[PDB]
Image: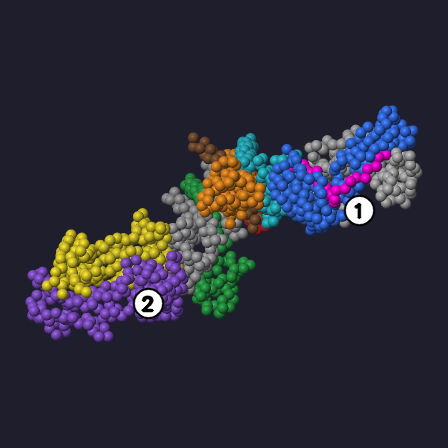
Chain colours: A brown, B orange, C red, D yellow, E purple, H green, I cyan, L blue
């Protein structure tokens, strides 16, 4: 059951990194929308 | 053992920092600085869970002089990721595919 | 190999879903 | 030293409420159950109740569940009874008796008390003294006083205990001057015994 | 509840003796019994518990025994500090039930009759007394006769416990009557009948 | 210590739900940003 | 006949004995009488509840029997075997409850999405 | 009487002097499975109520991470509600 | 005084004892002396290092004490307790490591998104 | 071993209703 | 059986270098510590140093750090000492002794070597100069072997037939030269020196 | 800094079958880490006791060890011909390990030496030197003082038969110094024998 813990924590930082990629794409698209409103 | 002033001993996730001295009061130091003063009748310091993996100097002192300081060094990982072939292959798969999808979406705001 | 294959199939299903919704919305909503 | 002490005589009118105290010393007061135990007529003993001093829970005799309320003051380490609607039947000697906290030691009462003699029946009636004249036997009768005691001495000897009749006490002394002192009514009579 | 009784309400035992005190329960109380010693001044202490054990401070002269419904306490080498009453308490069922307790040469009563004085006749009453001192045992009947007729009303009996010197009892038997009722009769008599009887009389006139 | 392992599984599920929600909202946002 | 109620909530185990109604109840652990000891305050016997705080599994588990006031520890023949974990801020559920909460999240998210779209449409 | 429960080799069972008369719970030597499935039961022979909580699917959630995940799920579904509000 | 240096890579744990420099270091584990000619060739000794490969949790975790030659195991001024979970190719993800990989991922995402935006900008 | 399968089943449910919409709109 | 066998008696000069070997047998050689011990003056034992045969690390006495260098050939299970720049203090009996490998049992030496007599001397080989000794006036006769090098010499009386009441004293050194005495009580004193290949049969006559 | 280990007795007088004790004095407290070894006169050193009390494998039970702190002892009963040897003590705390001077066993009644004086031979006079020899054979105990009136001294090991000692004292001069004096004398004390040139 240690191996499932290793894959779980590897997926934890992998999905945190994927969340960071989606967050920064949301940040660029928010800057684009704010430039569109101005 | 009791000889050589090695009175600090280590026995759930939490672990017991047991000291062999007089059972009245134990002044317990970490890294040579005052941290704990445990009274009757508790004698086993709980450093936390072994998942928290505490490290460093721990020593006890009773009515006599201070005991020889013992290092604790736990490596119960609970944050350790493994570099097998499939794991790093999946990491590169996720990284390359996510970068590709964001690049495709960013390309599609060419206008 | 169950959890790693589960995350792999999660990513594959994510990719299939985003591709199919991009195709569906783009071809059936014009531009 | 472990000791349980109680209050005084506590003359209480019938139908009223009485407070009987018990100070505990020499031990952890909350760590031992305090029973209260009734002695009626000087001969018959009856268990009346118990109180846990730590938790305040009281378990009563079903005869005395409506005649006693047990309280505990842990700051002064004193266990109290308040007896409710007491009659002249409840004139008895009440002891505080220490037993164990738990069920293995709560059936024997190890440290008892001196006793509170709640005599209930009447005001401080002044006594009436009568000489008794025919070895030779002489006597002195102290009738119609309330309550006990009277310190009867001869010339400043059998002192019989006082008996109640119509809520007046009667005492006799056998042996010449009879001296009677009653601190309740503040009476001090000295009578010389002479033959008829 | 369970009735807890003692067969011997009073017993006679000499100084330095081993004597037994018997206790009977209505049902079997599984040897959950404690004996207590109450000295005549008022203080009471735990003598033994669980029908066999010994409390701290209690010497080894007190030994309990018994089982089922029949229990006993045996006391050896009875001293002057051992003169007391003994109590068996069940510790089996609530409420705990105690018993009546036991209390621990053949002399004659010095019966002296006493007429009332002139103070009491001016007070309105009349108490005729009879003193019965230094006699043994406690079993006695005091019969009062007014003018040769037996009377039962107004009898007040005061017994004094056994002294450490003579080991005997002192009885005071009093009759209280009105002054007009006292003047209606002339001969007042008290008789001490035990098993022989000693009588003493006086005349009012 | 299966409790920490199962907690890690539960927060992996929570982060995966968060990823699904942000992927859906970011797809909707880019569809709007190419949909005037 | 009435069984005990055991509620394990973090580093705290609650034992309730409902067979004896309203009588003063004292507790026994492995033929050692506990509850209201006036020391070691992590165990307490307030009302019907033994509240054992920081429940050490190796030393606070085993037999547990309640008895009313005036009943011996040795004539009560209804014993409880207690053995439990003491994981801090830690509770127990299977796949069913986490599936239930994620299904609840799906339901409220889809309902809010449809409701917001319909409200903005009208 | 006091019925002993044997817990050996990760196996919990009962060993009484007579036939065990079960009344309520998990149904001379009567088995009860392992000790990790949490057996609960009431038994009386010539009464013990065993209640085991060796948890096998317990989660140890700290309040810091589970509140952060929930409050960022709330801002996720508020953003997705902010999505379709901008759609219409 | 000078603390023990424990370096764990994969399943190999190396214990270093920087106190008593120069002198020969002998090692005792669970009051049994190891680091010499034994049947287990995994437990090896160096000028300072004690190397344990194929480390196992339930027997090789315990009380390690380094002592110089001639001095007793009880005469050491130190002790060490070690309980380690080891696996193949496992690294602990420390706070500095995760901060560095997330900041280099943020930097490479910003740079690559700028590049694939400007590729479409030149294709506009 | 089970919870991730529920998340993948939810994504499969979204994908299959999306594919059903694509099939109904492609004819 | 467990035994340590060393080299023979060895002979060097001041400022030279000497090598002593020690074969270990009957036990696991690399699982035990070797100890070189020096016995000087015929009385005092001095522990010179210790060898770990496995790791090759050697711990030296602070007096004998530069006076010895300790090596081990593990293929033949043999220990070695090299004394560098020997002086007159280094003519001693040298011992290899096996102690335990670890600190629990390295402080006591279980088995020892037989010990090698190593001699340091400025001079060279000298043939003997035996002469008899008669009284000037049970009669005691003597035989003095003075002015020879090296040890040993055996003195027999009348080709070994006369052996009762014979006291052959151990030799002593002066001016880097040995002298030795023999006493008989009663005759031909026979002296054999294989180092100088000398065989002297000196008949004893009164003066 | 090093432990100056010393033995109180460097030569012990005993007898066959006796019981004797040997006392070793540690300079510092050494936690019962003493060892006792036996060096026979041929040169063989063997371990007898380690850790102040523990017998080795193969040592006879007549050897026993005791003591604590800075003072330890060897008790040996029923001395044999093999047991006559020099007994050493060694500390075990801190490097270097240090031995003491040792305690040899001496095995009788006081006896007078057989004193024999010998003039230089004519062979040595033709060689050039002149050596006057004095054999003090079979004297007990080993302590003796030899005075030469007008120096090399070689003792003897204690014999297994007579249990005594022998000493050879020789004085060597040149021919000119020997011819300068006429009377020569050597004297032993603990009997005077002399000659004339």
Q: Tell me residue D8's x, y (percent).
A: 24, 53
| Chain letter behind tag 2 | E
Q: Quadrant of the N terminus of chain E?
A: bottom left
Image point (12%, 74%), residue name: E148
* D55, above or below I77, in the image: below
Q: Tell me residue L25's x, y (percent).
A: 64, 39
| Chain letter behind tag 1 | L
**Residue span colored magenta:** L94-118
Residue E80 occupies which quadrant of the picture? bottom left
Q: Which residue is mark 2?
A: E13
User: Residues under labels 2 and 1: Cα distance?
Assistant: 94 Å
Q: Is B69 placed left or right of L139 in the picture? A: left
Q: Which residue is mark 1?
A: L161
Image point (16%, 62%), residue name: D139
Image point (48%, 35%), residue name: A27
Residue I101 occupies which quadrant of the picture? top right
Q: Is residue L9 magenta?
A: no
Mark 2 against mark 1, which lies toward the viewer?
Answer: 1
Disc 1 on helix, strand or loop?
loop
Disc 2 on helix, strand or loop?
loop
Image point (55%, 40%), residue name: B68
Assign the magenta stretch its main secondary structure.
loop
Q: Is residue L113 magenta?
A: yes
Q: Tell me residue I48's x, y (percent).
A: 65, 37
Give the number of marks: 2
Can residue E6 be seen here? The reply is yes
Q: Is E4 placed left or right of E190 in the picture? A: right
- Given residues I39 and E111, the one toward you in this image is E111
Residue L43 occupies which quadrant of the picture? top right
Q: Residues within 10 Å of mark 1 (few under 14, many from 20)?
A: few
């Amino acid at each position: 059951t240690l191996l499932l813990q290793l894959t779980n924590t590897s997926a934890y930082y992998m999905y945190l990194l994927l969340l960071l990629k989606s967050v920064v794409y949301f940040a660029i698209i928010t800057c684009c929308l704010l430039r569109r409103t101005a | 053992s009791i000889k050589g002033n090695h009175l600090v001993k280590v026995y759930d996730g939490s672990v017991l920092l047991t000291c062999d001295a007089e059972a009245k009061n134990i002044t317990w130091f970490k890294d040579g600085k005052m941290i704990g003063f445990l009274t009757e009748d508790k004698k086993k310091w709980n450093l936390g869970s072994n998942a928290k993996d505490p490290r460093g100097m721990y020593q006890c002192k009773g009515s006599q002089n201070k005991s020889k300081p013992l290092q604790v060094y736990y490596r119960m990982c609970q944050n350790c990721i493994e570099l097998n072939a499939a794991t790093i292959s999946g990491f590169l798969f996720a990284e390359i595919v996510s970068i590709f999808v964001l690049a495709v979406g960013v390309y599609f705001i060419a206008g | 190999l169950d959890p790693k294959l589960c995350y792999l199939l999660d990513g594959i299903l994510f990719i299939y879903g985003v591709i199919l919704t991009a195709l569906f919305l783009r071809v059936k909503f014009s531009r | 030293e472990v000791q349980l002490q109680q209050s005084g005589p506590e003359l209480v009118k019938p139908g009223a409420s009485m407070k009987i105290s018990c100070k505990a010393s020499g031990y952890s007061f909350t760590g031992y159950t305090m029973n209260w135990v009734k002695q009626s007529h000087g001969k018959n003993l009856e268990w009346m109740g118990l109180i846990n001093p730590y938790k305040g829970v009281s378990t009563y005799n079903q005869k005395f569940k409506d005649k006693a309320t047990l309280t505990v003051d842990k700051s002064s380490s004193t266990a109290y009874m308040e007896l409710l609607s007491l009659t002249s039947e409840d004139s008895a000697v009440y002891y505080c008796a220490r037993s164990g906290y738990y069920g293995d030691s709560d059936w024997y009462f190890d440290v008892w008390g001196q006793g509170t003699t709640l005599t209930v029946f009447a005001k401080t009636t002044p006594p009436s003294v009568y000489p008794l004249a025919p070895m030779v036997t002489l006597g002195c009768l102290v009738k119609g006083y309330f309550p006990e005691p009277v310190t009867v001495t001869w010339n400043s000897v059998h002192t019989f205990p006082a008996v109640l009749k119509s809520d007046l006490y009667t005492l006799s002394s056998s042996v010449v001057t009879c001296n009677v002192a009653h601190p309740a009514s503040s009476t001090t009579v000295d009578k010389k015994i002479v033959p008829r | 509840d369970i009735q807890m009784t003692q067969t011997t309400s009073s017993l006679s035992a000499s100084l330095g003796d081993r004597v037994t005190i018997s206790c009977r329960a209505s049902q079997d109380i599984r040897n959950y019994l404690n004996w207590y010693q109450q000295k005549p001044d008022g203080t009471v202490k735990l003598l033994i518990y669980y029908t066999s054990r010994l409390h701290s401070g209690v010497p080894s002269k007190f030994s309990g025994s018994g089982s089922g419904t029949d229990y006993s306490l045996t006391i050896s080498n009875l001293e002057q500090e051992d003169i007391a009453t003994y109590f068996c308490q069940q510790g089996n069922t609530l409420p705990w039930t105690f018993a009546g307790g036991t209390k621990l040469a053949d002399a004659a009563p010095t019966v002296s009759i006493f007429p009332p004085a002139s103070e009491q006749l001016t007070s309105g009453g009349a108490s005729v007394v009879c003193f019965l001192n230094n006699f043994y045992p406690k079993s006695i009947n005091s019969k009062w006769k007014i003018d040769g007729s037996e009377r039962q009303n107004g009898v007040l009996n005061s017994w004094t416990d056994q002294d450490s010197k003579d080991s005997t009892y002192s009885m005071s038997s009093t009759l209280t009557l009105t002054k007009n009722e006292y003047e209606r009769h002339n001969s007042y008599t008290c008789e001490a009948t035990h098993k022989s009887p000693i009588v003493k009389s006086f005349n009012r006139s | 210590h299966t409790e920490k392992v199962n907690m890690m599984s539960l927060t992996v599920l929570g982060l995966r739900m968060l990823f699904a929600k942000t992927v859906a909202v970011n797809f909707l946002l880019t569809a709007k940003l190419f949909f005037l | 006949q009435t069984p005990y109620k055991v509620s394990i909530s973090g580093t705290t185990v609650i034992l309730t004995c409902p067979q004896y109604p309203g009588s003063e109840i004292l507790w026994q652990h492995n033929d050692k009488n506990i509850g209201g000891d006036e020391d070691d305050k992590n165990i307490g016997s307030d009302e019907d509840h033994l509240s054992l705080k920081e429940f050490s599994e190796l030393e606070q588990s085993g037999y547990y029997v309640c008895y009313p006031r005036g009943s011996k520890p040795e004539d009560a023949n209804f014993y409880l075997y207690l053995r439990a974990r003491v994981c801090e801020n830690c509770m127990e559920m299977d796949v069913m409850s986490v599936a239930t909460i994620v299904i609840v999240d799906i339901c409220i998210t889809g309902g809010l999405l449809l409701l917001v779209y319909y409200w903005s449409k009208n | 009487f006091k019925i002993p429960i044997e817990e050996l080799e990760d196996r919990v069972f009962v060993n009484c002097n007579t036939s065990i008369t079960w009344v309520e719970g998990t149904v001379t030597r009567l088995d009860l499975g392992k000790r990790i499935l949490d057996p609960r039961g009431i038994y009386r022979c010539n009464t013990v109520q065993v209640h085991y909580r060796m948890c096998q699917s317990c989660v140890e959630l700290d309040p810091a991470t589970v509140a952060g995940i929930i409050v960022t799920d709330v801002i996720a579904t508020l953003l997705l509600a902010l999505g379709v509000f901008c759609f219409a």
